[PDB]
Image 1 (cartoon, each protein chain N blue to C red):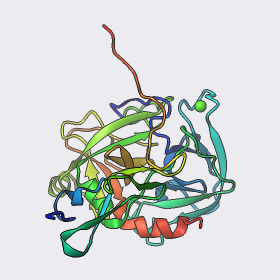
Image 2 (image 1 turned 60 degrees about the vertical axis):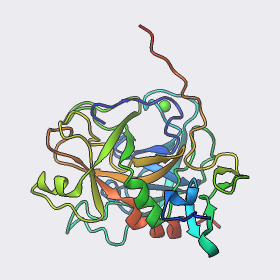
Image 3 (image 1 turned 90 degrees about the horizontal axis):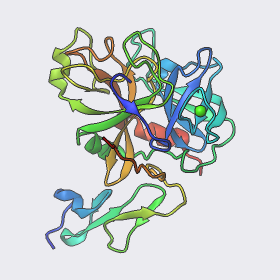
Length: 235
Length: 62
Ligand SMILES: [Ca+2]
């Protein structure tokens, strides 16, 4: 996150970090004790990923961290990186052993399709992660967060030579300076509704980070909630 | 009387579904239950989703 602020401990208790061949390479969100939602571009069937919940500062021990192995990776069935790296940029991770929920390790709420979209249209969400704090810069040690406004679709289309699909949304600032960045992928874009946070997006992609006239692009979660609910059901 | 999901979400804090005679039924996501007022949502489990349970209390001085 470029131009954000340090989170407080427990401020984003749904946030997880993914470690793999590279540490802290991507983020995620807790769906429930057994399941994480992240970005498909972060993952792939059989490469060794560990999830850490309850994390704050990625180099120190807070004694709130919960480390789990991933037993199954479920990229969305429409995701196909050979055709488009960021369309349908969403995947599910099944943990081997459940998380123990507490004030530092709490799921994000996920509404139905209609309400997810209603929430997204409130137009202000929070993004968070341990990604780069400048384009091509250093990553964060302490979890960073940023409030980002929703950007009008037509405005977003006009800003780029790339294609923004209907299962994507744009958020950020016209003047630059504040954005999600490399290493934040997979983490949550959440909307707070009367004090309860709901997942509205997945951090996905962008052209550089925080540049004037460019926006962050996010997976539109409302398009995937039925699939999330069906794959992640515990009962 | 005049209450509807099309206007102010039926006064429901979370979710609204229209009921007979221009009444609504409010509801909540998993881990919450409807409060006494049949509008608001309150936790029904110890660590319900989407809730920040650690105090954010902080302050900026000079
Ligand atoms: Ca730590």
